[PDB]
Image (cartoon, coloured by chain):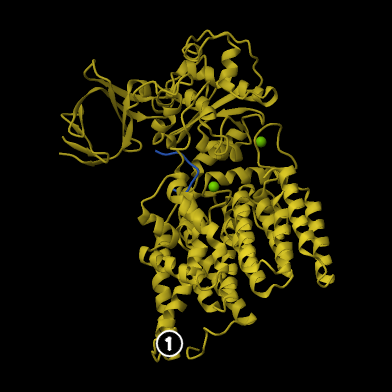
Chain colours: A yellow, B blue
Amino acid sequence: ELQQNFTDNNSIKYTCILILIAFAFSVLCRLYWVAWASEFYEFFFNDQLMITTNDGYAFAEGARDMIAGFHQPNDLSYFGSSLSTLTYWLYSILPFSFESIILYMSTFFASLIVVPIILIAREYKLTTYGFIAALLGSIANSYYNRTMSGYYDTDMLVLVLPMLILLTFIRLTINKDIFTLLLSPIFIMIYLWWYPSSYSLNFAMIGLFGLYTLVFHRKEKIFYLAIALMIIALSMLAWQYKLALIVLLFAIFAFKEEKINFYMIWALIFISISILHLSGGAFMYFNVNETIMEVNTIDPEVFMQRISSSVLVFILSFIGFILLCKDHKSMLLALPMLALGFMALRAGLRFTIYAVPVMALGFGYFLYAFFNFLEKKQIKLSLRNKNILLILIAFFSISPALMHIYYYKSSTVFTSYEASILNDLKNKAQREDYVVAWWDYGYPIRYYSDVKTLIDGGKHLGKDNFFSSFVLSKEQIPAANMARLSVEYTEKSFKENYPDVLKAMVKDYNQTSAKDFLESLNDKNFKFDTNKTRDVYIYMPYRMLRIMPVVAQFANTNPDNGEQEKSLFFSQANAIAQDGSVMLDNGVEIINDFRALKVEGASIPLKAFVDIESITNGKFYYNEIDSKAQIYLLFLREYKSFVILDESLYNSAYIQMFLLNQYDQDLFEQVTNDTRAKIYRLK
Amino acid sequence: GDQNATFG
Ligand SMILES: [Mg+2]
Ligand SMILES: [Mg+2]
């Protein structure tokens, strides 16, 4: 059991048992969050847990539509998407419900990385260390997080595929066996299919592979053939030309023994790169980039963590990677994927992922590395002891990622309540009907309602967010006007191809600027030169409260000149203490009988205090204070939650029509009403 | 954190 030599074993059977254990383990772990989120009712729909990233419903939707047979005209469905396609294959191949497939797919597929980890390890005659590099790599924070049992987004193979490509590269370097020639341009293709954006990453890995062929291999044949086939796999050529051209250029090389000279290969290279060439190789709005969670920044603490779940382990891993490299050279071929992770630090939070698997092999090597110092600096160490030491070093370094997984308990994109509200919305609304909501929501809104939306997590530039921002944060009447004009003109963009929709409306209402247009959606009696084609809704859920500032900013940003119109003072927080001095999270207090706030030392007069007791019914008590102030304090007793507004947010169609349940009845109709969310419709 | 959502 424990006295056997595991280090020096690199056998088929062994490698596959370690792949089995590694994989099974990486799956068991994704699978605690299910052990936890099932005892919670708010997390279920159609008798199964729901998805964990907005992004997901993009594909879900799409796939569902693929399962139907068709998606509608000009609604933005991901019918045919990589992920959609694969879900809809595995669906018609399996006895499990869409929701459960959609659910566990992430868990399955992303556990595959555990395979190239230990395989590459094994190329380096270090399998057992690979096993470790992969237990670690299949759990590390960033990776787990973007790959939970819930995460039905493109991310499940984003690191499996290039990591396969790289073991491909290396196996070519070492064994120079021809099967590699078929695999890397195949992998490189699949990756490119199943994530259009891996483009640059692939380009880069190929560049490297070439400069590297030039250094360490400027003589070997197979290699230029490979650069050329990879390069062909990169370009944009009907799948058939690729598969074909590859297979011919393969057989000729396997069965033509040796007879091909450099010049004709450099012509294959030049030619192929020509294929590449033939293929490809004023109105200002607020910026959606200082706004996306997934792309927020980091304190290098969490950088390290995210990449390896332990700063000490990060410092061990970096070193292990350095030695591994300047001990093997091929591992050098990982550099791009390292760099991407590091790009995180200035590019985004969501990039650390790229640097997990590599920095794991690194770590693995360091153990080998280290266990050398011992055996090689003369240190009699028996096998019982070496194995116990390995197992402990390992459990020790992995446990942090375990802990993180325990502590990492997401809810769902939405709760049952919200879903079912939307589903209910399906049977009331027509498939061509537009729903105005914020972009965070658009996907779910769509998967659950089959409706069309103005903006989604994909269509969410400042220019696109402007409308949904406006309808939701400006005054009721003008909001009610945007809704109409934004939906209609968004449906017109689909034929007349407006580069700037807002500008379209403007030039189509003979207004000289954009503030003259917008200060003009006020007057309830509004000319309508553009026709009514479908019914428009507006979804206003409690959840969007924490975001009201961020959402409002966009319409606050005057399309004419970048500038932010108003001041925007807003904040939602909870109570912690009372004597009558009440402390609020954000450091704001409520003092002298709900009249004034201590906002960083500054006492402030409340223009009033609103006390809302029934969101559903409209029952509140408007307390008047300092008629000559600007800051409103609200209390939602149904959510024991405090709010802090300024006049214009107090008057924004959302706070007005949701929190206070008051809405101009000749403009709207309250289609749905719940403490959790409302839905209105234009008349 | 890791989700294509708005904050904050
Ligand atoms: Mg995503
Ligand atoms: Mg549809």
Q: Where is residue A242 in the image (x, y as percent from the top left)?
A: 78, 54
Q: A198 or A52: which is nearer to us?
A: A198
Q: A367 or A280: which is nearer to us?
A: A280
| Residue A41 appears in the figure | no
Give the quarter the ligand 2 occupies. top right
Around disc 1, counting alpha carbons within 10 Å, would you say few (fewer than 14), some (14 to 19), or many (20 or more)?
A: few
Specify the subunit that label 1 lies on: A
Q: Where is residue A644 in the image (x, y as percent from the top left)?
A: 30, 30
- Helix or strand or loop: what does disc 1 sit on? helix
Above-or-below relation of A615 to A510: below
| Residue A238 appears in the figure | yes
Q: Where is residue A59 in the image (x, y as percent from the top left)?
A: 62, 46
Q: Count every numbered label the image shows and give the total.
A: 1
Above-or-below relation of A382 to B7: below
What residue sits 57% from the left and 18% below the top?
A503
What residue sits 60% from the left and 28% below the top?
A434
Above-or-below relation of A242 to A502: below
What residue sits 62% from the left and 46% below the top?
A60
Q: Within the image, what quadrant is residue A590 found in?
A: top left
What residue sits 51% from the left and 90% below the top?
A4
The quadrant of the image that shows the C terminus of chain A is top right
Residue located farthest toward the front when viewing the structure as drawn: A263
Q: Name the residue under label 1.
A: A375
Residue type at the position of mark 1: Glu
Q: Position of residue A332 (x, y in %)?
A: 54, 65
Q: Left or right of A452: which side holds A629? A: left
Disc 1 within 8 angstroms of ligand 1 (CB) = no
